[PDB]
Length: 94
Image 1 (cartoon, rainbow, N blue to C red):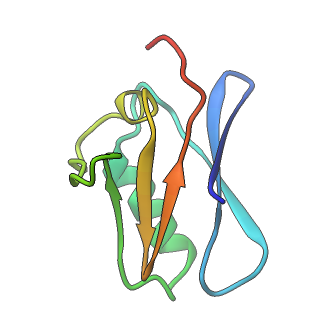
Image 2: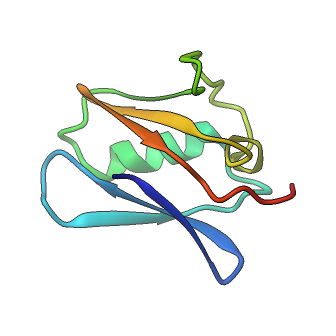
């Protein structure tokens, strides 16, 4: 799976990327990082990623400008190449 865990107050997203078996974790800043920033970090991590996107649980594409704080208010789907991951963050205030 893709997991979301808060460490030292910040969300840490751990992902399996297509080109290696070792998982990679991405620490994000909810107040300043955006969806698009995180997708760019993923692509920079693994050149074997041809395509990456995030969708709502209802399957609607999430805007790249959206803050990570808003994204982590509820579940989401993370598409990496031909795999879709249902991510379930821990629900926190805002």
